[PDB]
Image 1 (cartoon, rainbow over the protein chains, first blue to last red):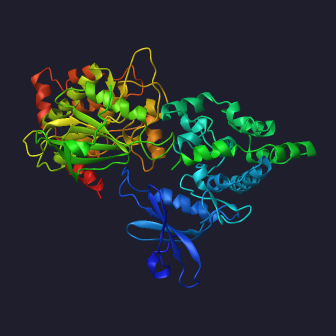
Image 2 (cartoon, rainbow over the protein chains, first blue to last red):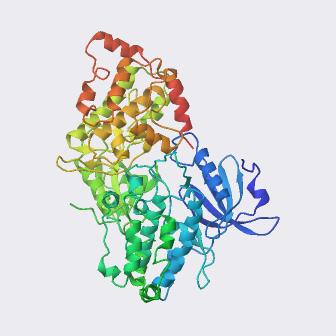
Length: 303
Length: 304
């Protein structure tokens, strides 16, 4: 249901480089007819199967197909799609506010109430996807972006659907991918996959946001994978001394091997840490603080 | 048992770039004291754990540790190891004859006998490693190099020990890594690992050498992995019509899920396709022919 076969330079003014990854190169641009600004993600095509360099026809078509389905305020949106010999270039919504974790590291101070405000935006985006039977499959702090950095409470935008995949019911889908720090046990063990995996990733992102520490990350990839498979973590009191039991329960109910016993997105929204029932839960959440001292320490180390 | 802490440029004249990967950049260089030529692999260090960019202290130390054990004509050899704020640089034997598969694609013609000549060199290298309880863990056509391209029968050198690991006996090793096209089922399934894995790789490498095709490679990674785990392949007669049964038996005994029932390096070397026992096995091997037609076709598609 296809791609524009024109030259993207005819219709857009490409300029500054925004941030290249391993397979794509993102650049700011400007539609000519309107003057509006977008991002332009130049994905590099593959050549024949098993060129290490590039991305396959099938997997670009998949990402573009999912992007078209996806209309939500907490999820990036696709404007147009061109292609040529070398690249397929996507004209995406310009999200120029930086990472979430970046903005949070700037923070003078940050309570668990303020923290859940950002978590909730994420849960809303992920709820929209999961309602449309889509699994992002690459939930991590790099892919959690801000539209405008200079707002009191900025607007989260989930990005990068390179690993996303529609889930059907009778159909199985097994594959190994992602960043080891943030993958569920079913990825590592090459077990059937679904929407559940995103809920694991959320439990991890939460853990790092509050404490600055990461639950399963070892010295080496080897260890990391052994930790995930064994579900070996703990709330080390050095970082989690100012963290609520509500917050810890949320994380603990997400970081669960059995996919069926793990929280759904609908259950995570209804969890009391995200949606307090009484006043005393609301106040515990207001008086609990994110560990920004240790969160800055670890976020600096990622550069 | 450490790294030189001096500036590598003081002692070596670095020059032309030779072939950067993702974590390392390799450059031709020249020892100043001797005038001799080496390859200098500049490995980029990590910063703190999970920087996607870099290589960890522990994993550089392991590569260097395995490199210092490794003395064989069919295996690259480590000369020196400097380091600095940014990189650990290894001074490795210069291997400048290109990949094996590249040389073979230049071939006028190539019989199974001539092919096993190169396969033997590979098995000899691998045997040496496996005798020293080392697993390469990254056997593939890119890491099978030639020393001098312009010789009738060139000299194979296994390279890149970035994934290599010493296998003990009681000790278990489980990890996920490598190139999907060439990993054994135990990698994919996160099952305990050892020397066997390399042998599966050799089976895949042989398969491609002979036919130009690849046994498990699918359209997407998803399919490739399913194919490995299911051990789903076949000898499509379009590519294997001029391939001997001996050749097909060797491959078939290596591409086996069960690690115990798979061929060991010693069993591979003794296999009749490698080591005939009568004259008629020898003749079948001379008269059977590598499919350079299809081999070139695919090897071209892997380019730039």
